[PDB]
Structures are given as structure tokens and as C-alpha cells.
Figure 1 (cartoon, rainbow over the protein chains, first blue to last red):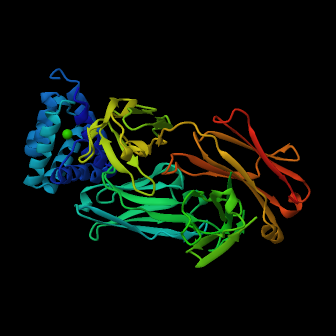
Figure 2 (tube, each protein chain N blue to C red):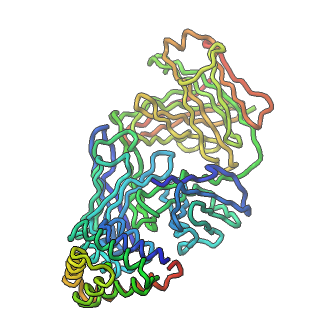
Figure 3 (spheres, rainbow over the protein chains, first blue to last red):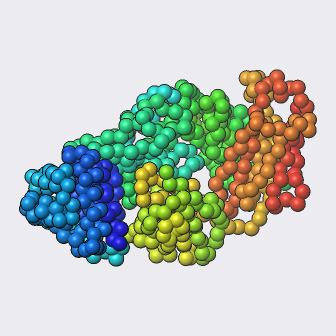
Length: 137
Length: 206
Length: 213
Ligand SMILES: [Ca+2]
């Protein structure tokens, strides 16, 4: 179910810029859309391996929930980008409430809010909108 | 337009070094991954290295790992490839290419790895008859061979050069002619080797 | 490391004919495959990306198809410009890997080679080396056997060969085989011959000489 999304997210989270450039080519992303996803990747790279591992735990437990392209997963991503830090972390808490996961949740969410402008936030969503409405998805 | 222009290739000895350059223009360089692809004489294409948009990550072919270093200067729109500990195997045309599937290539730059110094060739002579010259023990490529100062192009065959175990190249050029024009008419080959500034004329006769 | 197996490595066709080049990946690459055309002395040109998407400017007689592990490049109605070498390339993951190549060549009628043999010159012998060369002029197809014998001793490992590409006039090949010996070893044997076997000949042609002529 929606393989092309999870390949882009995995390419963002894993922190390798070259493998992300490959993903962005595969999904015909524009130069502003590329810029915005690389700023998201910087947050995983700056906050280390466990940011990938604990956010992978989060994305996994949402995707295998009762609620589940899953609208719960779509909702998680929009909150991560456009919601407030308390909104995102409280939403993550309903799926998994380990102190270390909520700690990691807030560290990433603060990073992207500090690092991305509103233009970058809008572009990440427009690139996501393409992915969600693709026939591959 | 989108232009990619390689430079820095040339002759190197085995063990030595080379820095290739690729000035790019016509697109926002920093948004895209660039690769280097190569091609040995009469062989296929081979991906050698790639580097991400801002240069935080790179990958290499196993044969080239640890020897080669790919890099870029995003302020100058230039891609680099420092090639160290070069081997006979690395002799090739090196192209820079945009993206991960190569929409735009450069015209390449040739890299030749050999122990040999630049050296001019020795030229030896060789119903319908055939005659020729054997062009021997030169380096590097290329050699060009015309016949009777370009006046005889009909039925002329010049062969791809073979790299001998000495490290020096060797080829032959042959032409077929009518049997009864042997003693009467002069058949001379003009062998130019522009790398050594050597030209050789060689008359051929039974 | 994804291996790309391209087949066949060679085919000869005519103008108007259909041409199908298969290419297969050792593991799945979804639709992330590209196709290239390369002419002598030139950089490759992109034809297809994403398995079946035609690059702009490329004529529509070129098409691609396939998914997963098996991919096809078909030319509908072959034109003179389309005689070239063709390559597949996966961009599913790094390292990026190419197929071995497929040479598309001009089909013509079978033609036997005119065999010649050239003794080493008196000039070369004085420098101290001896190169005997055997010419195979104007033939088709390329597949051809060339044995060397010195006093009937079947030779190997002391000769290399070069082949031209198809001639522009008549679509034929020419080959040379070059037996290289020292002056000392050369002058210890009398008779030198090259035996050429080829599709266009009913028996194998031999061509020889004695040192001294
Ligand atoms: Ca998330």
C-alpha cells in the first residue's frame, strides 16, 4: 500500500543525500520541492541515528494500527510540518507513548520548525500531494 | 542550453595522479546529483562515481573505492574527480553526466595510463593484389595513415591498434590494388603520429 | 550490486526490419531503467527513461516495455541512422550499472574473405624482431577462425588480431592477424602459414611462404 511514499520517507530519514537525490528524481520533484525535503533530511542527520530508529518506530506503529495510503499516516505528516510542537507530540502519544519516543518527537519537530520557512513547508506538502495522487500510490 | 565541459585528462604512469574537472552551466547545479561515467577502448559504459547536490554524500564503483575522490564546488558550478593510484585498467574516456539517468553528457576527456614515454612509430612495409605498412612500437594513440598523400583512398583499410605486452601500440594499414599495376606505379604510405611530432613516408614494392 | 544482462550482444538487420533488444536485471528495479544509443566517436544519447517514457526529440519508432526484472527496447521500422550500439542502465539503486551493449549492424549477403600473407620485411628483421601478418579482406559475417602454423606446429599465445567495423561502401569486415616472433626464433623455422576458416568458404583456405621466398 502506497510504496512510493515509504520509499521517499525512507530516503529522507536514512540521511544519505545521494540516495535522496535519487528518490527526488524518481518522483519528478521541482528544485524548490528538492530543497524542502533536504531540509527535512538535515534534521534526521543532525539528530543522529536514533532519530531515524525512533521515528521509524512511530511510522511503523501508526501504519499497523486499527486506523490503517492511510489517512492516519497522512495526518501524522501534516502535523509534523504544519501543526504546533504540542499538537504533533500529543498525536504521536496516542499511537506510542514511550518517554524516549516523545522526547525524539519534540526534538525533530523543533528542528524542522527552526530550519524550514513557510515556503519550504508548503513545497514539502505540494510534493507530498503529487505522491498521494500518483497511480503508483 | 545545458553544457558540460570536461578537462584535465591526459597521460599518466601507473601509480600516479590526475584531477578531472567539469564546468557545468544552463541549470541550477546544486539541486542535482552529478556522476562520472567511463569507457575503455572498444568496451561498454561503466559508472565510476557520483556525488549529491550539496556534496554531503558520494558513492564509487568497488574497483575505484579509496583511490578516487569525487567533489564539487557549488559556487563555481564545477565537478571534480581526483584520480589517484591509477592503473592500466583505468585507461578510458571519462564523461561527467547530470542526474541519475544521464539526460546530458559532456564530450568526454581521454585518460591513458602507461609506463611508456611518448615515442614515434617504426613503419615497415608489407587478379587483385594487396600491400601495406606495419606501424609498430608507438605511444600514445593515435596514428593516422594515408596512401600516396591522400590520392589513394579507394579500398584502404586501417586497423584498430592493438596494445602489445611491451606497453607500446601497433597497427597495420592495407590497400588492395589491381595486380598489373605493381612495378609501374608507386605505392607509398604516410604515417603521422602527432603526439611525438613524427611523420614517416614508406615506399612499398615487390 | 545489480547485474544487467543485455541480449543479444550482436544482431544484424536491414532497413525496415523490426529490432528487439532484451535486458534483464538480477533483482527487481521496478520501472527504473533507461536506454541509450551510441554511435562511433560520440557520447551516448538518451532514448527511453523510466522503462517506457520517450525522451523529447526521440522518434516514436523507439519504444520500451517491462517491469521488475525483464525489459525490452523495440525499434519498429529501422532507419539508416539507427545502426549503432545500444545500452540499458538501471537507476533503481547505487551503484548505477549498465548492460554489456548490443551492436546493431547492417545485414548483407555472405562474402568470403580474400586471404593474403605478408612476410616480415628485411628492414624489421635487421632491428631484431619478426612480425608475420595475415590479412582477411572484405567478408561477412565477422565470425572467422585464423590458425597459425610454423612447420605444421599449431600456434597460440603469440599473435593478436584486429577487426575493422563494417565498411561504409559494402558493409563488409576486414581482419588482420599478426604473428610476432624474435629474429632468432623466426630463422629456426622455414614454412609459415595462416589457415582461414569462414562461413563463406566451403573448405579452409591456407596461405603460406618459405623464408627466402
Ligand atoms: Ca514523522
